[PDB]
Image: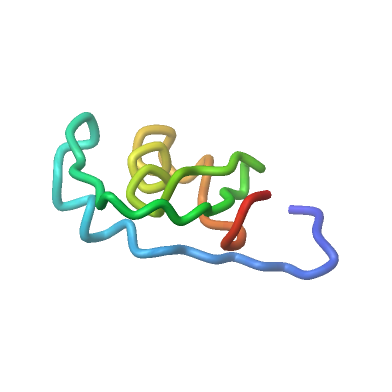
Length: 66
């Protein structure tokens, strides 16, 4: 992984990992998060759904829009 600042962040996907990957209930709160795949997600729940789906392809990079 090429980065100046090696930032391996992992948001709590565990609580959502408790649900089936296709059906993960998300909060009504919108909190822009950015995945390591450089994709901005609506919140950590949505990030987690894709994170599990693509199996760590998209991990948590930083909070906020990419």
